[PDB]
Length: 184
Ligand SMILES: O=C(O)[C@H]1CCCN(C(=O)Cc2ccc(F)cc2)C1
Figure 1: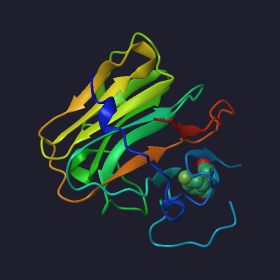
Figure 2: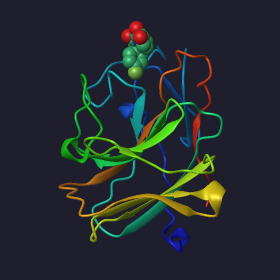
Figure 3: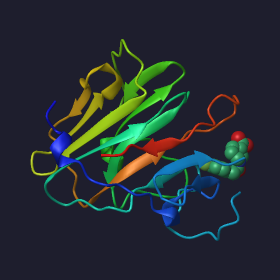
Figure 4: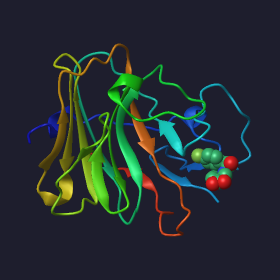
């Protein structure tokens, strides 16, 4: 792919984070803490270890990269600014999410129902491309020379978009590693 020139500098929005997350001083890394002594607010994801990027996108082409090295479970993509924050929900375009994930040694796209991904080289870094006007979200395997993972097309965004992250639970003791926004 030749999307690298649409690179944007993403930072995490502390105020949206689940109360167990630890965001680095530079707002470029997030991990599961083992409650982080913050007040509750209506923006925080309550049920899952999720956080949003601070940036909002309503036009144009945007590209960023995320490091997932040594994690067992995570979700990545974009979502509407107005997604539900409280209680249980599924990650689907109907609920305002365009995501992929790793879970139990399989990769899947967040369609409803979910779609099996075919990845021969487990990624250490994921590239995410959004074309707002075209209604496209695409995912790339940076570890495998940028190979395509998945394209959501005919997307109905229906509002501003935010970068979306889930570090996953760490019931196993094998999923403590952070998500990291990789430099341009
Ligand atoms: O499985 C369980 O009982 C624990 C899971 C994580 C810790 N638990 C909490 O209630 C607090 C919490 C909830 C959601 C979240 F994303 C992060 C922290 C219960």
